[PDB]
Image (cartoon, rainbow over all chains, first blue to last red; front, side, top):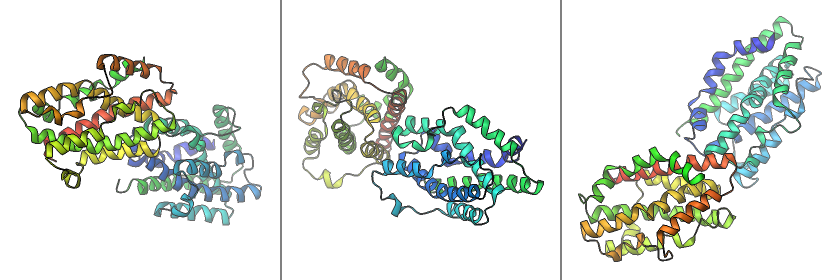
Length: 209
Length: 209
Protein backbone atom coordinates (compact mmCIF):
# COMPACT_ATOMS: atom_id res chain seq x y z
CA UNK A 1 0.00 0.00 0.00
CA UNK A 2 1.41 3.35 -1.20
CA UNK A 3 -0.27 5.42 1.53
CA UNK A 4 1.45 3.42 4.28
CA UNK A 5 4.80 3.45 2.48
CA UNK A 6 4.60 7.20 1.95
CA UNK A 7 3.98 7.69 5.69
CA UNK A 8 6.94 5.52 6.65
CA UNK A 9 9.32 6.73 3.89
CA UNK A 10 8.79 10.39 4.78
CA UNK A 11 8.65 10.08 8.58
CA UNK A 12 12.02 11.72 9.36
CA UNK A 13 11.58 14.70 7.02
CA UNK A 14 7.96 15.11 8.13
CA UNK A 15 8.78 15.20 11.86
CA UNK A 16 11.53 17.74 11.26
CA UNK A 17 9.33 20.07 9.18
CA UNK A 18 6.46 19.97 11.68
CA UNK A 19 8.78 20.68 14.60
CA UNK A 20 10.54 23.66 13.02
CA UNK A 21 11.11 26.50 15.51
CA UNK A 22 8.84 28.81 13.49
CA UNK A 23 5.82 26.46 13.45
CA UNK A 24 6.50 25.45 17.05
CA UNK A 25 6.56 29.10 18.23
CA UNK A 26 3.56 29.96 16.05
CA UNK A 27 1.40 27.14 17.45
CA UNK A 28 2.37 27.92 21.08
CA UNK A 29 1.27 31.54 20.64
CA UNK A 30 4.74 33.09 20.84
CA UNK A 31 4.56 34.97 17.52
CA UNK A 32 1.66 37.06 16.17
CA UNK A 33 -0.84 37.53 13.33
CA UNK A 34 1.97 39.22 11.32
CA UNK A 35 3.94 35.93 11.24
CA UNK A 36 0.84 34.00 10.33
CA UNK A 37 0.20 36.43 7.48
CA UNK A 38 3.83 36.08 6.25
CA UNK A 39 3.36 32.28 6.27
CA UNK A 40 0.19 32.61 4.19
CA UNK A 41 1.82 35.00 1.68
CA UNK A 42 4.62 32.47 1.11
CA UNK A 43 2.03 29.68 0.91
CA UNK A 44 0.11 31.71 -1.74
CA UNK A 45 3.29 31.68 -3.88
CA UNK A 46 3.92 27.93 -3.65
CA UNK A 47 0.21 26.97 -3.87
CA UNK A 48 0.09 29.01 -7.05
CA UNK A 49 2.97 26.94 -8.47
CA UNK A 50 1.66 23.68 -7.05
CA UNK A 51 -1.74 24.18 -8.69
CA UNK A 52 -0.25 24.99 -12.11
CA UNK A 53 1.58 21.64 -11.81
CA UNK A 54 -1.62 19.90 -10.63
CA UNK A 55 -3.54 21.44 -13.59
CA UNK A 56 -0.95 20.15 -16.07
CA UNK A 57 -0.81 16.60 -14.69
CA UNK A 58 -4.61 16.35 -14.40
CA UNK A 59 -5.00 17.58 -18.02
CA UNK A 60 -2.49 14.92 -19.09
CA UNK A 61 -4.94 12.28 -17.79
CA UNK A 62 -2.79 11.17 -14.81
CA UNK A 63 -4.25 10.49 -11.28
CA UNK A 64 -7.45 12.36 -12.22
CA UNK A 65 -9.60 11.23 -9.28
CA UNK A 66 -6.85 12.08 -6.75
CA UNK A 67 -6.32 15.58 -8.20
CA UNK A 68 -9.74 16.88 -7.05
CA UNK A 69 -10.05 20.58 -8.08
CA UNK A 70 -12.18 21.15 -4.91
CA UNK A 71 -8.78 21.03 -3.11
CA UNK A 72 -7.48 24.19 -4.89
CA UNK A 73 -6.27 26.68 -2.23
CA UNK A 74 -4.67 29.55 -4.18
CA UNK A 75 -7.79 31.71 -4.72
CA UNK A 76 -9.17 31.00 -1.24
CA UNK A 77 -5.78 32.00 0.16
CA UNK A 78 -5.75 35.27 -1.83
CA UNK A 79 -9.13 36.15 -0.22
CA UNK A 80 -7.70 35.33 3.23
CA UNK A 81 -4.73 37.61 2.50
CA UNK A 82 -6.98 40.46 1.34
CA UNK A 83 -8.68 40.27 4.78
CA UNK A 84 -5.45 39.79 6.82
CA UNK A 85 -3.66 42.58 5.00
CA UNK A 86 -6.78 44.84 4.72
CA UNK A 87 -6.14 45.63 1.06
CA UNK A 88 -5.54 43.84 -2.19
CA UNK A 89 -2.06 45.25 -2.64
CA UNK A 90 -0.02 42.67 -0.65
CA UNK A 91 0.35 41.19 -4.11
CA UNK A 92 2.88 43.80 -5.18
CA UNK A 93 4.89 43.68 -1.95
CA UNK A 94 5.38 39.96 -1.43
CA UNK A 95 8.31 38.07 -2.85
CA UNK A 96 9.51 34.45 -2.47
CA UNK A 97 12.03 33.69 0.27
CA UNK A 98 15.05 31.67 -0.85
CA UNK A 99 13.42 28.32 0.14
CA UNK A 100 10.17 29.28 -1.57
CA UNK A 101 12.13 30.16 -4.77
CA UNK A 102 13.65 26.65 -4.66
CA UNK A 103 10.27 25.00 -3.93
CA UNK A 104 8.53 26.95 -6.70
CA UNK A 105 11.34 26.14 -9.15
CA UNK A 106 10.87 22.42 -8.47
CA UNK A 107 7.07 22.72 -8.83
CA UNK A 108 7.53 24.53 -12.17
CA UNK A 109 9.93 21.79 -13.34
CA UNK A 110 7.26 19.24 -12.43
CA UNK A 111 4.65 21.26 -14.32
CA UNK A 112 6.79 21.58 -17.49
CA UNK A 113 7.89 17.90 -17.42
CA UNK A 114 4.25 17.00 -16.62
CA UNK A 115 5.81 14.68 -14.03
CA UNK A 116 2.79 12.85 -12.62
CA UNK A 117 4.51 10.76 -9.88
CA UNK A 118 6.49 13.79 -8.58
CA UNK A 119 3.25 15.88 -8.64
CA UNK A 120 1.42 13.25 -6.60
CA UNK A 121 4.20 13.42 -3.97
CA UNK A 122 3.75 17.20 -3.65
CA UNK A 123 -0.03 16.90 -3.62
CA UNK A 124 0.11 14.41 -0.72
CA UNK A 125 2.48 16.58 1.32
CA UNK A 126 0.48 19.81 0.99
CA UNK A 127 -3.18 18.75 0.70
CA UNK A 128 -3.24 15.71 2.99
CA UNK A 129 -1.40 17.92 5.52
CA UNK A 130 -4.04 20.63 5.08
CA UNK A 131 -6.90 18.11 5.42
CA UNK A 132 -5.27 16.40 8.43
CA UNK A 133 -3.84 19.22 10.54
CA UNK A 134 -5.72 22.23 9.14
CA UNK A 135 -8.44 22.50 11.80
CA UNK A 136 -5.71 22.36 14.46
CA UNK A 137 -3.73 25.24 12.92
CA UNK A 138 -6.94 27.21 12.29
CA UNK A 139 -8.07 26.75 15.92
CA UNK A 140 -4.63 27.86 17.06
CA UNK A 141 -4.70 31.03 14.95
CA UNK A 142 -8.04 32.01 16.52
CA UNK A 143 -6.93 31.05 20.05
CA UNK A 144 -3.53 32.72 20.00
CA UNK A 145 -3.87 35.56 17.51
CA UNK A 146 -7.59 36.32 17.32
CA UNK A 147 -7.69 35.68 13.57
CA UNK A 148 -11.15 36.22 12.04
CA UNK A 149 -12.50 32.76 11.06
CA UNK A 150 -13.47 34.41 7.76
CA UNK A 151 -9.74 34.93 7.10
CA UNK A 152 -9.08 31.23 7.61
CA UNK A 153 -10.81 30.12 4.40
CA UNK A 154 -7.57 28.27 3.55
CA UNK A 155 -8.33 25.71 6.31
CA UNK A 156 -11.91 25.15 5.13
CA UNK A 157 -12.77 22.87 2.17
CA UNK A 158 -16.11 23.91 0.79
CA UNK A 159 -18.04 20.97 -0.59
CA UNK A 160 -16.02 18.38 1.27
CA UNK A 161 -18.89 17.38 3.56
CA UNK A 162 -16.85 15.10 5.86
CA UNK A 163 -13.05 15.33 6.20
CA UNK A 164 -12.66 11.89 7.82
CA UNK A 165 -14.28 10.10 4.91
CA UNK A 166 -12.38 12.27 2.38
CA UNK A 167 -8.98 11.50 3.91
CA UNK A 168 -9.73 7.79 3.97
CA UNK A 169 -10.79 7.92 0.30
CA UNK A 170 -7.69 9.96 -0.58
CA UNK A 171 -5.45 7.21 0.87
CA UNK A 172 -7.36 4.56 -1.09
CA UNK A 173 -6.88 6.56 -4.30
CA UNK A 174 -3.14 6.62 -3.49
CA UNK A 175 -3.23 2.83 -2.99
CA UNK A 176 -5.07 2.39 -6.30
CA UNK A 177 -2.71 4.41 -8.49
CA UNK A 178 -1.04 2.22 -11.07
CA UNK A 179 2.69 2.92 -10.74
CA UNK A 180 5.75 1.12 -12.04
CA UNK A 181 8.54 0.55 -9.50
CA UNK A 182 10.44 3.40 -11.19
CA UNK A 183 7.49 5.83 -10.79
CA UNK A 184 6.81 4.71 -7.21
CA UNK A 185 10.44 5.23 -6.19
CA UNK A 186 10.43 8.63 -7.92
CA UNK A 187 7.26 9.61 -6.04
CA UNK A 188 8.61 8.43 -2.66
CA UNK A 189 11.90 10.34 -3.04
CA UNK A 190 10.00 13.46 -4.09
CA UNK A 191 7.72 13.30 -1.03
CA UNK A 192 10.74 13.56 1.27
CA UNK A 193 12.05 16.46 -0.84
CA UNK A 194 8.64 18.17 -0.50
CA UNK A 195 8.74 17.87 3.32
CA UNK A 196 12.30 19.28 3.22
CA UNK A 197 11.22 22.29 1.08
CA UNK A 198 8.48 23.06 3.59
CA UNK A 199 10.91 22.79 6.50
CA UNK A 200 13.16 25.35 4.78
CA UNK A 201 10.14 27.63 4.11
CA UNK A 202 9.53 27.69 7.90
CA UNK A 203 13.22 28.27 8.58
CA UNK A 204 13.19 31.32 6.32
CA UNK A 205 10.04 32.59 8.02
CA UNK A 206 11.56 32.24 11.52
CA UNK A 207 14.87 33.90 10.64
CA UNK A 208 15.74 36.86 12.88
CA UNK A 209 12.48 36.70 14.82
CA UNK B 1 -18.91 32.28 34.67
CA UNK B 2 -16.20 34.17 32.75
CA UNK B 3 -15.15 36.54 35.54
CA UNK B 4 -14.40 33.56 37.81
CA UNK B 5 -12.69 31.52 35.05
CA UNK B 6 -10.67 34.61 34.14
CA UNK B 7 -9.47 35.05 37.72
CA UNK B 8 -8.65 31.31 37.95
CA UNK B 9 -6.95 31.06 34.54
CA UNK B 10 -4.70 34.08 35.28
CA UNK B 11 -3.89 33.24 38.91
CA UNK B 12 -0.28 32.09 38.45
CA UNK B 13 0.76 34.91 36.10
CA UNK B 14 -1.13 37.46 38.29
CA UNK B 15 0.62 36.28 41.49
CA UNK B 16 4.06 36.52 39.79
CA UNK B 17 3.21 40.02 38.48
CA UNK B 18 2.05 41.15 41.93
CA UNK B 19 5.18 39.86 43.67
CA UNK B 20 7.82 41.67 41.58
CA UNK B 21 10.73 42.95 43.65
CA UNK B 22 10.34 46.43 42.20
CA UNK B 23 6.68 46.78 43.17
CA UNK B 24 7.25 45.07 46.52
CA UNK B 25 10.11 47.50 47.29
CA UNK B 26 8.10 50.52 46.03
CA UNK B 27 4.95 49.72 48.03
CA UNK B 28 6.69 48.98 51.32
CA UNK B 29 8.69 52.22 51.17
CA UNK B 30 12.21 51.07 50.25
CA UNK B 31 12.31 53.14 47.04
CA UNK B 32 11.12 56.70 46.42
CA UNK B 33 9.36 59.31 44.34
CA UNK B 34 11.96 58.90 41.58
CA UNK B 35 11.08 55.22 41.08
CA UNK B 36 7.36 55.90 41.25
CA UNK B 37 7.86 58.59 38.56
CA UNK B 38 9.80 56.13 36.30
CA UNK B 39 6.87 53.70 36.67
CA UNK B 40 4.33 56.35 35.70
CA UNK B 41 6.38 57.45 32.66
CA UNK B 42 6.41 53.85 31.36
CA UNK B 43 2.71 53.61 32.24
CA UNK B 44 1.99 56.69 30.14
CA UNK B 45 3.58 54.93 27.14
CA UNK B 46 1.49 51.79 27.51
CA UNK B 47 -1.80 53.51 28.49
CA UNK B 48 -1.44 55.67 25.36
CA UNK B 49 -1.22 52.41 23.29
CA UNK B 50 -3.90 50.65 25.35
CA UNK B 51 -6.36 53.55 24.89
CA UNK B 52 -5.81 53.68 21.10
CA UNK B 53 -6.71 49.94 21.03
CA UNK B 54 -9.71 50.56 23.30
CA UNK B 55 -10.96 53.40 21.00
CA UNK B 56 -10.63 51.12 17.94
CA UNK B 57 -12.45 48.18 19.54
CA UNK B 58 -15.19 50.43 21.01
CA UNK B 59 -15.75 52.08 17.58
CA UNK B 60 -16.11 48.58 16.08
CA UNK B 61 -19.08 47.90 18.38
CA UNK B 62 -17.51 45.19 20.55
CA UNK B 63 -17.89 45.17 24.37
CA UNK B 64 -19.17 48.78 24.25
CA UNK B 65 -20.58 48.79 27.82
CA UNK B 66 -17.28 47.54 29.24
CA UNK B 67 -15.11 50.10 27.45
CA UNK B 68 -16.24 53.07 29.56
CA UNK B 69 -14.41 56.23 28.39
CA UNK B 70 -14.42 57.37 32.02
CA UNK B 71 -11.57 54.87 32.56
CA UNK B 72 -9.18 56.74 30.20
CA UNK B 73 -5.92 57.45 32.08
CA UNK B 74 -3.43 58.83 29.54
CA UNK B 75 -4.37 62.56 29.82
CA UNK B 76 -4.69 62.42 33.66
CA UNK B 77 -1.36 60.62 33.79
CA UNK B 78 0.39 63.23 31.62
CA UNK B 79 -0.72 65.92 34.11
CA UNK B 80 0.59 63.79 37.04
CA UNK B 81 3.88 63.56 35.17
CA UNK B 82 4.01 67.32 34.60
CA UNK B 83 3.69 67.68 38.40
CA UNK B 84 6.19 64.92 39.28
CA UNK B 85 8.76 66.19 36.76
CA UNK B 86 8.11 69.90 37.21
CA UNK B 87 7.60 70.52 33.49
CA UNK B 88 6.75 68.96 30.12
CA UNK B 89 10.43 67.88 29.66
CA UNK B 90 9.54 64.24 30.22
CA UNK B 91 7.68 64.08 26.88
CA UNK B 92 10.81 64.38 24.78
CA UNK B 93 12.99 62.58 27.38
CA UNK B 94 11.17 59.32 28.06
CA UNK B 95 11.75 56.09 26.16
CA UNK B 96 10.07 52.68 26.32
CA UNK B 97 11.94 49.99 28.27
CA UNK B 98 12.48 46.71 26.36
CA UNK B 99 9.51 45.27 28.27
CA UNK B 100 7.30 48.26 27.41
CA UNK B 101 8.36 47.98 23.74
CA UNK B 102 6.95 44.43 23.68
CA UNK B 103 3.81 45.47 25.57
CA UNK B 104 3.14 48.47 23.31
CA UNK B 105 3.79 46.23 20.25
CA UNK B 106 1.07 43.86 21.46
CA UNK B 107 -1.40 46.71 22.10
CA UNK B 108 -0.70 48.14 18.62
CA UNK B 109 -1.27 44.71 17.05
CA UNK B 110 -4.60 44.38 18.92
CA UNK B 111 -5.51 47.86 17.61
CA UNK B 112 -4.52 47.05 14.01
CA UNK B 113 -6.36 43.64 14.00
CA UNK B 114 -9.25 45.28 15.93
CA UNK B 115 -9.08 42.24 18.25
CA UNK B 116 -11.97 42.72 20.63
CA UNK B 117 -11.47 39.66 22.87
CA UNK B 118 -7.76 40.48 23.21
CA UNK B 119 -8.52 44.11 24.05
CA UNK B 120 -10.99 43.12 26.78
CA UNK B 121 -8.28 40.92 28.33
CA UNK B 122 -5.80 43.87 28.49
CA UNK B 123 -8.56 46.23 29.64
CA UNK B 124 -9.45 43.95 32.58
CA UNK B 125 -5.84 43.50 33.67
CA UNK B 126 -5.03 47.24 33.69
CA UNK B 127 -8.27 48.99 34.70
CA UNK B 128 -9.59 46.43 37.17
CA UNK B 129 -6.06 46.46 38.71
CA UNK B 130 -6.14 50.27 38.95
CA UNK B 131 -9.53 50.18 40.66
CA UNK B 132 -8.06 47.79 43.27
CA UNK B 133 -4.24 47.50 43.65
CA UNK B 134 -3.63 51.06 42.39
CA UNK B 135 -5.75 52.40 45.27
CA UNK B 136 -3.23 50.91 47.73
CA UNK B 137 -0.43 52.36 45.59
CA UNK B 138 -1.80 55.89 45.77
CA UNK B 139 -2.18 55.71 49.58
CA UNK B 140 1.37 54.38 49.98
CA UNK B 141 3.03 56.91 47.66
CA UNK B 142 1.57 59.68 49.81
CA UNK B 143 2.32 57.94 53.13
CA UNK B 144 5.79 56.52 52.42
CA UNK B 145 7.25 59.18 50.14
CA UNK B 146 5.15 62.28 50.72
CA UNK B 147 3.92 62.41 47.09
CA UNK B 148 1.26 65.10 46.85
CA UNK B 149 -2.17 63.67 45.95
CA UNK B 150 -2.21 66.28 43.14
CA UNK B 151 0.34 64.02 41.39
CA UNK B 152 -1.78 60.90 41.96
CA UNK B 153 -4.75 61.81 39.71
CA UNK B 154 -4.04 58.55 37.84
CA UNK B 155 -5.52 56.63 40.79
CA UNK B 156 -8.63 58.74 41.03
CA UNK B 157 -11.45 57.97 38.61
CA UNK B 158 -13.41 61.22 38.39
CA UNK B 159 -16.17 59.60 36.45
CA UNK B 160 -16.66 56.84 39.01
CA UNK B 161 -18.73 57.46 42.14
CA UNK B 162 -18.58 54.02 43.85
CA UNK B 163 -15.62 51.72 43.15
CA UNK B 164 -17.21 48.64 44.80
CA UNK B 165 -20.34 48.82 42.66
CA UNK B 166 -18.22 49.60 39.58
CA UNK B 167 -16.02 46.51 39.97
CA UNK B 168 -19.02 44.23 40.58
CA UNK B 169 -20.81 45.58 37.49
CA UNK B 170 -17.65 45.24 35.38
CA UNK B 171 -17.47 41.54 36.25
CA UNK B 172 -21.15 41.06 35.49
CA UNK B 173 -20.58 42.61 32.02
CA UNK B 174 -17.71 40.14 31.50
CA UNK B 175 -20.09 37.33 32.43
CA UNK B 176 -22.60 38.63 29.85
CA UNK B 177 -20.17 39.22 26.96
CA UNK B 178 -21.14 37.01 23.97
CA UNK B 179 -18.07 35.12 22.76
CA UNK B 180 -17.40 32.07 20.58
CA UNK B 181 -15.39 29.29 22.29
CA UNK B 182 -12.39 30.46 20.29
CA UNK B 183 -12.83 34.12 21.29
CA UNK B 184 -13.19 33.04 24.92
CA UNK B 185 -10.01 30.97 24.74
CA UNK B 186 -8.24 33.96 23.11
CA UNK B 187 -9.39 36.37 25.79
CA UNK B 188 -8.12 34.00 28.51
CA UNK B 189 -4.76 33.53 26.74
CA UNK B 190 -4.27 37.29 26.28
CA UNK B 191 -5.14 37.95 29.95
CA UNK B 192 -2.27 35.76 31.12
CA UNK B 193 0.02 37.49 28.55
CA UNK B 194 -1.09 40.91 29.90
CA UNK B 195 -0.08 39.98 33.47
CA UNK B 196 3.26 38.70 32.16
CA UNK B 197 3.85 41.97 30.22
CA UNK B 198 3.27 43.91 33.39
CA UNK B 199 5.55 41.67 35.40
CA UNK B 200 8.26 42.36 32.82
CA UNK B 201 7.69 46.13 32.97
CA UNK B 202 8.30 45.92 36.76
CA UNK B 203 11.42 43.75 36.19
CA UNK B 204 12.82 46.38 33.84
CA UNK B 205 12.05 49.19 36.34
CA UNK B 206 13.80 47.17 39.07
CA UNK B 207 16.77 46.76 36.75
CA UNK B 208 16.71 50.51 36.07
CA UNK B 209 15.92 49.75 32.41
